[PDB]
Image 1 (spheres, helix red, strand yellow):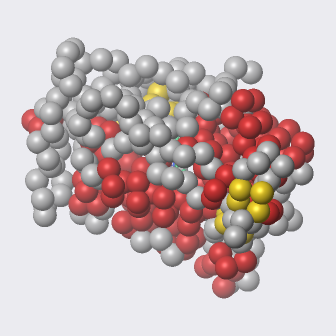
Image 2 (cartoon, helix red, strand yellow):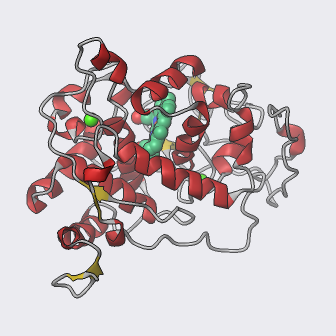
Length: 345
Ligand code: HEB
Ligand SMILES: [Ca+2]
Ligand SMILES: [Ca+2]
């Protein structure tokens, strides 16, 4: 059957027991009592920037293409966090390092762990998986491997296809993370502008809101990779805006609107896949029973809605197969999306 940890919990594999002490430590000292706040969002982002930096095409040509989910972004933070796509990630890397040192775990395992635990904090999240077995990187990733907000949809599709054999529909899946996300470094005048009106809730509001006609910048204009957004305080990036309207991806983008089961099943899958880049999944240990049970979305709303002051008339419909769903609109005046201030220091 199962192993029993010193704290009296039971697990599928005895090696998983050490992660309960990591869990308690980060929930209290990294995530401010298990919150879906700035440190959680940064930890989710960090998983992608560690993991996607792998390139089988470069290896085939005799060039080191990076080791994927290997902890390189932490081990070699002075190198990798100075790459422009990794802007702002040295803060979370620095917050995470003490825990890795204290608990004697691999940097790559800890990054995957912290991302899973972060998502567990966000109502609506899938039940996140956690596998161990990522040896420390011995070489930093090359630059040019992490997508930018100003890149073409073509080059982003190509990049994820190379990194993980991900198709263009799976690209849409992994962008679900922007449902619990804010932007600190794109607008030099303001930090913490969310991508959707519910950055604390893993829902499909990101997929709704990116489909709306953009009307204004939330702060300054003229920032590379930024386009007009539909709501005060919400930011929109060019890549997301284009993927939402591109004939290859627009139908998948819309499919998440008012479809919670598809959202969570697809994201659960793709997040695990990201955390196993550069690894042999058969060689890894399943420690998924350490991750907290995800919480349902509270309250009494339909799963997807238009934000207040928006209706079907504000949607730029892009899926030729299926009209955009006629959602309910939240009552009241158009409200400003509140910023998520990044960690002090
Ligand atoms: C994980 C998963 C994921 C994925 C896949 C992604 C994908 C992406 N993305 Fe992301 N992001 C994210 C998650 C993510 N993401 C998050 C979580 C965030 C937030 C952070 C904070 O809040 O801090 C972001 C954020 C972000 C930002 C902001 C930053 C700064 O400012 O610093 C940007 C620009 C981006 C982009 C992007 C792109 C281009 C792509 C393509 C693919 N993003
Ligand atoms: Ca890496
Ligand atoms: Ca959200």
